[PDB]
Amino acid sequence: PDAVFGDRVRRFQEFLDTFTSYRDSVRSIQVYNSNNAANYNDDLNILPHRIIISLDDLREFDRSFWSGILVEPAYFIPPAEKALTDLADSMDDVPRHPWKLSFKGSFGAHALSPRTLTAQHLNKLVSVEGIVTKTSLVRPKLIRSVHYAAKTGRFHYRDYTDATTTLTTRIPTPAIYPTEDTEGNKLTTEYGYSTFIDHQRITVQEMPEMAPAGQLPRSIDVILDDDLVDKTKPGDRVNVVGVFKSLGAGGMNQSNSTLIGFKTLILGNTVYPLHARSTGVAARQMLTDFDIRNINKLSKKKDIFDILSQSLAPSIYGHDHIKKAILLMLMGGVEKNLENGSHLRGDINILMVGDPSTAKSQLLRFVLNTASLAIATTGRGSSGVGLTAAVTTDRETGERRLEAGAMVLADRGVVCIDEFDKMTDVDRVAIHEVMEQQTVTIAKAGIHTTLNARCSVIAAANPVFGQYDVNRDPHQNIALPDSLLSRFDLLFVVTDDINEIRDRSISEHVLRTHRYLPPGYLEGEPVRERLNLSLAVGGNYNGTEIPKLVTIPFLRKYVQYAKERVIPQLTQEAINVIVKNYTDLRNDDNTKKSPITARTLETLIRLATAHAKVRLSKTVNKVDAKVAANLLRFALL
Amino acid sequence: MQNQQEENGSEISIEKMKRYITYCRLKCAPRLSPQAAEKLSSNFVTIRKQLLINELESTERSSIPITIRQLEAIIRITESLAKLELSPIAQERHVDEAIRLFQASTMDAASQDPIGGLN
Ligand SMILES: Nc1ncnc2c1ncn2[C@@H]1O[C@H](COP(=O)(O)OP(=O)(O)O)[C@@H](O)[C@H]1O
Ligand SMILES: [Mg+2]
């Protein structure tokens, strides 16, 4: 027993007393585990025994203890964990693993980067942001081994600890694996009674958006334990909160005698997968009951399909039907997985083609900025292996492995392809399978696999003559294969027609856009840039809290709520409308920009389903079918 | 001659220009005045009206196009001129010389196109 350890335990007990959010979070975890255990006993998931602790509240309570965790975490984190474990055991008397801590809040000088991590931050709690590059295989580490002596019929056990388990270094006592007891009888290892804890080691290097553009990047190893494994994948942007520790002796023993120095790594306490632009982490955000009530209130209005669409990009004049299409693509439709293995698309693909300076790249950048999982690519910039997948070799195992391209990483997301017309032929053959069958089939040397690539694709292209010509046929203007055009659900030809009143309207809209101030900025002060990192849980300017037009953070809340909550089903009253309109479209005499196939019918079904998602309606109504048809006739005629 | 002109003050040194452009970019980001918007809109519709009637008479598309990106180009030139004198707001005199420079750069290039001329 140590007096200062007990004093710090009592101080953290007072801290947990004055803030009850940690108390009823512990209640929530315990009642979830107990209810799952009772359901398993009568008729599942087990939450980890760890609690997020806010450093700001701790600084408000005790500045000395907060500075102790930040500066000397090895002396302050274990007393806090013991206090949390004692509190949990005191409130689990009526209904065994020790409770761990996790940290959120401002870190100040300890919010660092793998370049900025130096030896002055050793034995300190650091928050390090970066990109995950190498992710080791999750390996079980033996904690306690259980053995059986058949001659005595007795079960024995041995506990094992290493330097990474504990923040405070103790005497290394290597207890070997017992195969004979103290009487000499042979021991049989009891697999299944021994305990194993998952262990992982990830490599976090500095973000390419924040690394210097010339030189090599810096990386650090992070050790993760049983509940923190498999929270990241290579390519994720991450924030790791943990203790920066040094291990071993840096050649200062006789046996070691080399200048690796002291091996340095981060004992991970908290892993936040951050969402960045064009990455594999989807932006997910908390829906407060006020926002849910607001979403349900706007769901009841009749003009909502014209409010959400016009509030997409108010900085672009016109292109209203493209806004409708982008909104319906963000809604995403409903896919059908059948009992006989057949798959039907839900995702909606948009192709835009036409003259330059028609806000195509701007719309693609907006879709990149507003979607949860949008990934931006370019025709000649990416290749066939760039979009789908490629093959590499693992250093440890020595066997071939896969690197996921843009299409696999944007699964359940949006792929924004800029300058679609300049893609290579093998890339087109690759995207043919992805854009309909929703899969990437890899048949390379030795490995055969399929990867899920369920993606909405929005693409911008140019005509082969540079400007679209009215009198020429659309087949010569597009110059893309008919199967690829049939892949796209909506094809919008945008032409920069010159009219005096239209030109005046564009000019005034552009100038009113060009006379904007952010709040809290001066007349001559230049606007600053902060890189948008969002935590992934689980022409009027004054659009604020649903007045006339919807702000973008609420619009993505609406999109999130509609994608997670409502899954509409077809009704006959919409089906007759869709069937009649598809029959009219197949046999109409009017020349259309896009060919009419059986994919037009499923386009109609997906568009009606997306519009039903807009209204938050569990059934597809007739007005949904009418508006889904009328959006398609604008694209075709 | 350049040293004498630098001593007089009608030319400034290259390092002084470098640090002055650094200070201007980190300090001033001007705006268009509301009275300068009407002139920009009027001239941006007159040029495109001229191109429209020229394309209608010639029945052939012009080889050098004039678009909304050119309007924002003129805006950017005006705001650069206003950033020269560290002016938080751009007056009419910046707009006028931005127009004259746009005439000397893109409009004479378009007049070199026979489709863009014919007037
Ligand atoms: N309808 C419009 N409303 C507002 N700005 C526009 C519009 N059309 C073009 N622009 C402006 O013209 C510039 C050209 O970019 P963009 O039109 O996206 O190129 P592209 O047409 O090749 O995608 C953009 O910065 C955009 O601000
Ligand atoms: Mg473009």
Image (cartoon, rainbow, N blue to C red):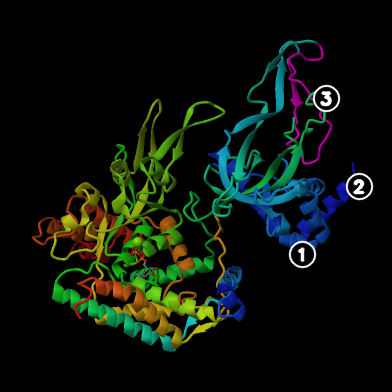
Residue at the image point whose x is 17% and y is 58% from the top: A474
* Mark 3: secondary structure: loop
Name the amino acid, label 2. Ala
Q: Main secondary structure of the magenta part?
A: loop
Q: Are marks 3 and 1 on the same chain?
A: yes
Q: Are marks 1 and 2 on the same chain?
A: yes
Residue at the image point whose x is 56% and y is 42% from the top: A133
- At label 1, counting other C-alpha atoms closer than 10 Å, the crowd grade (few under 14, some 14-19, many 20 or more) is few
Name the amino acid, label 1. Glu
Chain letter of disc 1 in the image: A
Residue lying furthest front in this view?
B1
Which of the two discs, 3 and 1, labels the residue nearer the N terminus? 1
- Which of discs 3 and 2 lies nearer the camera? The answer is 3
The residue pinned by badge 2 equals A3
Label 1 vs label 2: CA separation? 25 Å
In-image side of A303 versus A105 (left or right): left
Residues B13 and A88: in front is: B13
Which of the two discs, 1 and 2, labels the residue nearer the N terminus? 2
**Residue A257 placement (x, y as % from top left):** 79, 26
The residue pinned by badge 3 equals A254
Name the amino acid, label 3. Gln
Question: In the rendered view, would you say A448 is above or below A184?
Answer: below
In the picture, the quarter occupied by the N terminus of chain B is: bottom right
Residues A173 and A364: in front is: A364
In-image side of A313 versus A501 (left or right): right
In the picture, the quarter occupied by the C terminus of chain B is: bottom left
Residue A169 among those drawn in magenta: yes
Ligand 1 within 8 Å, label 1 CB = no
Question: In the rendered view, would you say A383 is above or below A600?
Answer: above
The residue pinned by badge 1 equals A60
**Residue A110 placement (x, y as % from top left):** 72, 54
